[PDB]
Image (spheres, coloured by chain):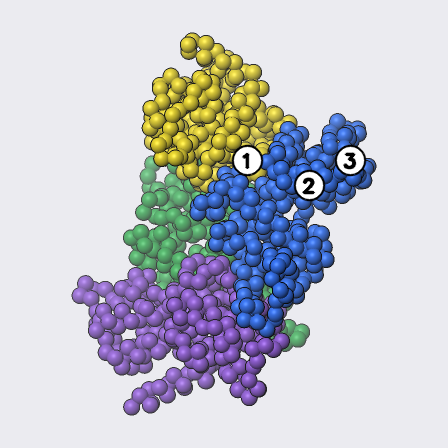
Chain colours: A green, B yellow, C blue, D purple
Amino acid sequence: NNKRWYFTREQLENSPSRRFGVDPDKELSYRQQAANLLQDMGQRLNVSQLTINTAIVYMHRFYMIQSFTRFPGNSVAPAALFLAAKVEEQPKKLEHVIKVAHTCLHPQESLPDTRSEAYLQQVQDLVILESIILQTLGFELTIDHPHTHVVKCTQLVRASKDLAQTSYFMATNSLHLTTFSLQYTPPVVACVCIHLACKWSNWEIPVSTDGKHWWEYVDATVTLELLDELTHEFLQILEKTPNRLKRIWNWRACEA
Amino acid sequence: NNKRWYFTREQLENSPSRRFGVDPDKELSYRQQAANLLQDMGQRLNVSQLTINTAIVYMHRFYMIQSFTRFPGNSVAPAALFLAAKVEEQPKKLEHVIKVAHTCLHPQESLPDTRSEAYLQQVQDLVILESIILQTLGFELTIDHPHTHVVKCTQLVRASKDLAQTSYFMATNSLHLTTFSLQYTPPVVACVCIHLACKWSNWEIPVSTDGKHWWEYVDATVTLELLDELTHEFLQILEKTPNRLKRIWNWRACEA
Amino acid sequence: NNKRWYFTREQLENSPSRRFGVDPDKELSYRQQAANLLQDMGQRLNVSQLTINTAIVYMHRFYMIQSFTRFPGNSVAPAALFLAAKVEEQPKKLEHVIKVAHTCLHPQESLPDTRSEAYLQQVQDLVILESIILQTLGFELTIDHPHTHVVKCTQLVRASKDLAQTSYFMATNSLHLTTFSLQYTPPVVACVCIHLACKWSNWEIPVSTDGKHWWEYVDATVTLELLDELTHEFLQILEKTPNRLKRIWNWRACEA
Amino acid sequence: NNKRWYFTREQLENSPSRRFGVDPDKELSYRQQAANLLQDMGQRLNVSQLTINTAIVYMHRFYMIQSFTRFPGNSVAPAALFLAAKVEEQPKKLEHVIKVAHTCLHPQESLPDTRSEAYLQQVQDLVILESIILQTLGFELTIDHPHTHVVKCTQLVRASKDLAQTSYFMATNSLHLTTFSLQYTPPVVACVCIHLACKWSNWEIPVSTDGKHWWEYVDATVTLELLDELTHEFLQILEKTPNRLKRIWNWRACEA
C-alpha cells in the first residue's frame, strides 16, 4: 500500500533528515513531539481517531521526502492536518486548526487576530503548504492505518474487554512512536498491536478450526517469528521514551 | 525534452475533454482562447515574453487530463501564471495575478476585495489548483522552447531582422493558436516557424559548404517534407482562425 | 497497446538505424523488403494469414530499439516468423522455420544438410535472435489488427464483398508498406485501409440517423480530415513505389 | 543495485512461492540449496568465485517475480550461471554449462549426447529461459557484491590475513544462505560479514582518530544497533542451516 512507501533501511536512515544534518537520535523526538500536538491540537475539534492518524502519516511520510531544516514542523501539522482533517468526512476551516495552534503552541503569548500581522503568513505558508505536501505524497488519498482489521478481529475471534480493549491502543502508539508507517503495512502492523495484548496478559488466543494461528487473519504472510520481532521492536521506543511509556506503565491499571 | 507530454491521437482527439461532450473545435477554441487570458493578461503585468510562453505550455498540458467545462481557463490561467512566473525568476503576487484577472475577465464589474469571501474563497483555490497543475505536469518544470533556437538559427545564418521578427513572431502562434507544444519538439517547432516565413517573405537561405542543410543544425532529424508538411497545418491552423489570422495579416500591412 | 509502439513522427524519422547512416526511405526500404521475408516466406509454411501479420508487427517493432545495419532482416525474419507462430497457438519446427529460409534466401544452392558443418554453426543463431527479440518485446504476444474491425465494419454497414477485399488487401500495405502500426492504433488504422478502398470502388455508406458518421461508431475520436490525411498519406506513400503499386494496380486487372 | 530490488520483510514473507504452495522455510531451502548447485557446480566450470557470486544474486531476485514451483533451479542455475559468466569476461559454452549440470546433478546417469532430443530440447530453453530472466531482471546485469568493501576495508585498517579470510569467506554465505541481496546493500552487507568474524575471531579494529567508527567509512549509513541486528540475524540463519554452518565452522579447525 502501495509498496513505494515501504523500502528497507536503505531509505530508512537515508531520509532527508537522516542525512541533511540530523542525527538519528534527533528524529524519533522530532516526529513524536510534533506528533504529540497532532493528538492534542487535533484532539480538540472533536477530531476522530480517524482524523488523528491520517495526519500522523501526513507528517511522518511528508517529512519522509521533506526536511525539518527548512519547514515549520510544529506548524506543519496544520498542513498534514489540513488535508487529513479535510480528507476525512469532517473537514474544517483556515483558522479552526490554526487558532488553537496558538493555544497548544503559544500557551502564554497574547491573543491572535485575523487583521493582525499574524494569520497572514500563517494563511500564507500553511495555506500554501497544502500545495507543498500532496505532490510529494503523489496527490494520493489512500491510507488505511493498521486498525480496521484489529477492530475487526475482535468479535469474530471473540476477544474480551481487556484484550480487544487493549487492541485499539497499540496501533495508535505505533503511529506516535515507531516507523512502521513507511515500512510495515497496516495489516502486519495489526497482528503486533493485537499481539501486545496477549503478549501482555498471555491470552494466547487459541488456534483456529484447523490449527490455524490468529495472526493469519489480518494478513496471510504474518508469521510468528517475524511478528515476534516486530513487537519486540515496539519494546525499543517504549523502553526509552519516558513520556508515554509511563502511560502504558499504568494505563493497564483499569480493565480488570 | 520529455516523453510524457507527446501523445498520439491522443491528439487531443480522445482527451478527457472529449469524454464529456465538447466539440473538437471548441476545446481547440478553449486552448487558444485560454492563451488570451494569459498572453493579454501577462501583458498587463509587464512580464517577460518568455515568462508567458511557458505559461501557455502548462495550460495546454493541464487540460491533457482535465476539461475546460469543469476547470475553466478563465481562472486556470493565473494559476499557471504562478508556476511559470516564479520559475522564470520574476513572479508576481497571487493577488496581482488575480488583480489582472478581474480587469481582464470582468473589465466592468467593480474592483474585487481582499477581505471578501468572493476573493478568499478562490484564494486557497489558486494555491490549491496551483497544486492540481503543480503535479499534473509530473512536477516537470524543465521545458524547451522554439524561440531560443530561432534566434541562433537566424543569427548563425545571417538572417535579417524584419524577417527574423517573422521567425520569432511565428513562434508565438505555435503555442497560443496551435497545440504544437504537445505534438512536436522545440528543435522541431522552430524549423516550422522558419520554413513558413521563408515563403511569406519569398526567401531561400544560402547554406552550408559541408553538404548539410540549415534545418539540420537546430535538429539533424528534421525533414523537408515534414517542414512543408507542417507548414500546411500551421498556416491552415491560422487559415481558419479568422480572429487571430487577419490581425496577423494586418501586421504585415505596414511591413513593406 | 499503450505506447512505445506508437512512436512520434519525430521518433521514427530518427530511428536508431538513423544514428548509423540509413535513409528514412532506405530503412523504409529495408523494412518492407524485410517484410517480404515474412509474408512471402510464411506463405510457404501454410501459416495463418494473421499469424504472419503479427510477425511483421514484431519485425516493425524489433527495430524500434535495434538496427538494420547490425541485424539484417535477411535473418531476423525467421526469428520473428517464430515468435509469431508459437504466439498464434501454432508454432513451427526450428528446422522447418529455418528450412524455409534457404529456399527463400538461397534459391539456388543444392539442398542443405542437417548434419553439415554449414548447418550446425548457424543453428543457435535462430535460437539466439529469437530471445533477443522475444524479450525486447516484453513478451507482448497480445496485438490487435486493423482487419477484424475491417471485417465487421464492412458488414455492419453492409459494404460489398469486392470492396471488402479491397479493404483486407489494404492492411498488407498499411503494415508491410507503411509503418502505420507504429503511428496509429488498430481501430484507427483500419479506417485508413477502408477510407482508401471505399473510394476506389466508388462507394458511399449511408449512415447514422443521429447526425454522426460511420467512422465515429467504430471510433468516436477518428476524423475525416485525419481519415483523408492518412488515406492521402497512404496513397501518397504508394506514389513512391512504382514497383508494388503496378502489381497492386494489376491485382484488380481481373476484377476491375 | 539499483532500485526495486530490495524488498521489505513482510514483502519477503509474501513471496511468489507463498501464493502457490511453498513453506516459508521451504522456498528459503530452495534458494540456499540452489546455491549449492552454483558454487560446487561452477567449480566444474572452473569459474571465478565472484563470477558465481553474481549468479546466486540473479536466482535470489528472479524468484521475487517468478516461482520455484514452475521454474526448477535444476536448470535455473545453469541459466543464471550463463548471464554471470559472460558478464564476467570469461563465460562458458551453452553446451558445457549444461554438460556441467549433469556431472553435478546426475553423477550416475549416462553421458549426455550433443545430437539428442534431450540435449537439443533444453538447448532452446537455456536461451529461452535465459531470456525470461534477461527480461525479468529489468535487464539489470549489473549487480554489486558484499566482497569489494570487505577487501579494501581490511586493507584500509591494515587487518591481518587470518582475519581477512574470516571477512571474505563470510561474504560467500551472506549470498547463498540468506537473502540480504534483496534486503540490504553491498556497503551494508560487507559490514555484516565483518561484524561476525569480529566476534568469531575475537577482534575489534581501532580506527580513525576523529571520534568516528569504521562502519561509517564502508558506509556512512550503517549503525551498530543494526550491526548486531544483522550479525544476530546471520548467526541464527546458519543455526537453521546445520549443513553450511559446521562446514564454515570446521574451516577454523583445519585452520590449524
Q: Are marks 2 and 3 on the same chain?
A: yes
Q: Which residue is mark 2?
A: C247
Q: Is residue C23 shown left or right of residue D211?
A: right
Q: Which residue is mark 3?
A: C256
Number of the label disc, if any, that sits on residue A177: none
Q: Work out whether residue D5 or residue D108 is closer to the camera in this orientation and state it.
A: D108
> Which element type, helix, strand or loop, lies under badge 1?
loop
How many residues crowd around disc 1 within 10 Å: few (fewer than 14), some, or many (20 or more)? many
Q: Quadrant of residue B22?
A: top right
Q: Which residue is mark 1?
A: B64
Q: Badges 1 and 3: C-beta atoms under 8 Å apart?
A: no
Which x, y percent locates residue C75? 56, 57
- Distance (Cα) linking label 1 and label 2: 44 Å
- Distance (Cα) linking label 1 and label 3: 47 Å
Which x, y percent locates residue B169? 43, 21
Q: Quadrant of residue D43?
A: bottom left
Q: Work out whether residue A210 or residue D74 is closer to the camera in this orientation and state it.
A: D74
Q: Image point 46% across, 51% down: which residue?
A: A57
